[PDB]
Image 1 (cartoon, one colour):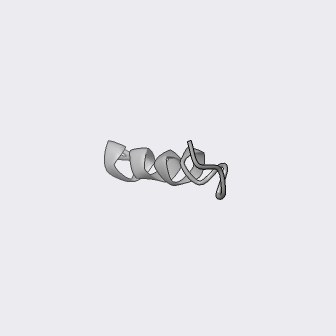
Image 2 (image 1 turned 45 degrees about the vertical axis):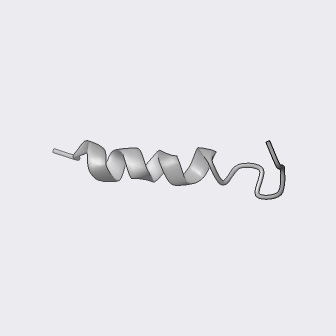
Image 3 (image 1 turned 135 degrees about the vertical axis):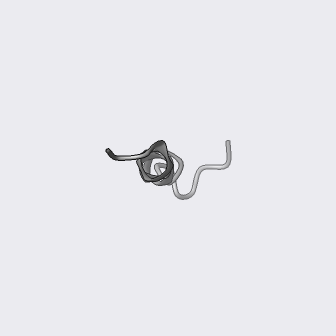
Length: 24
């Protein structure tokens, strides 16, 4: 159960939105 589709996209939309302002 729990595919890597939602599991991956889950954290993917958390670590990438960490800075929310920083350039690089």
